Image (cartoon, rainbow over all chains, first blue to last red; front, side):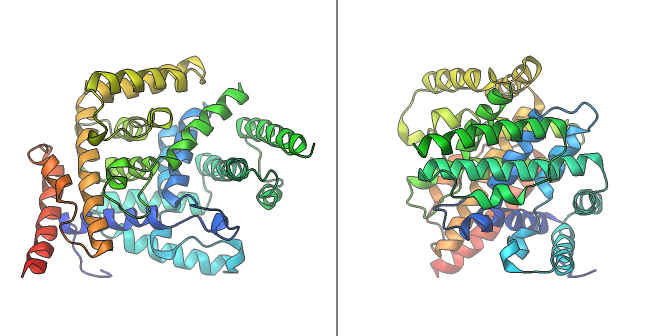
Length: 195
Length: 188
């Protein structure tokens, strides 16, 4: 084993406590931009999961998309939310999160360890159409939230850096249309504020 | 279309800014959001065993059941809102929220909410037990974080006898034993 915490009720409860730490990991991107009361990582995954339900693609297993949305950032309960500004090399971030996912999932019975760990791997390696879709949900959810913070602050355009970072990251036809609509509305508000 | 979908998602996003009222009224610092609560419930649906249940349906129930709160807010027992009035408000809200979706999705999400509201399936009953379990777990977590063991006992008292799912009963028993050991320790 790694540790010897067993696969009974005590470890299931501890798994749930670790998952609960996600409520107390603020999303670092917003922290570093001085957003007041920023969302948690679980807030972020929650809306992604709903987005997987309501943004259509008949070619995808949406049950799997929902599960991927709910599991993909789970390592952050241990690792925290590493942002670009933290300058952690991709390989190191991978190593930390993989080791964390091993620690987290080993608290579960073998069948559930396997499922959750394999969901995480599917997302990390972007090995499926479902994974690639969910990654675009993540980026879309982020820029939507950016626009929402700008609106709440009455500072249109303040969080432009987030939009710039999503350049050429979108290709799913439904998400592309959602993003175009979002950027149009936002840009309308920016222009309206300018006059 | 995309515009209405965006409007729907902004409404859903409001859940991030609805604090769970039970904790607010107990002076918890930085209390969890309603979406925080549904998030962990959804993960619980995945990891708490029941081979008789449609688990992905349980996941969706967890993610939809409190969704009306984006318009209604999180009504707590201390708010003294009659059951019928709360139901009326949340039903009206869900109709408003879901009407922003295309037909098939409007129907699905509304029917999920309704299934949980009316507790009309084994899945709904399971998810209601997840909700209560998630709540008392969070109560003990705040007690631990505050270093005020037992402070939120009222939440435990409110769930007394409300658990009957065998796996959830096991988890709850473990939780209460660990917590009571902590309280007993503090009491000495």
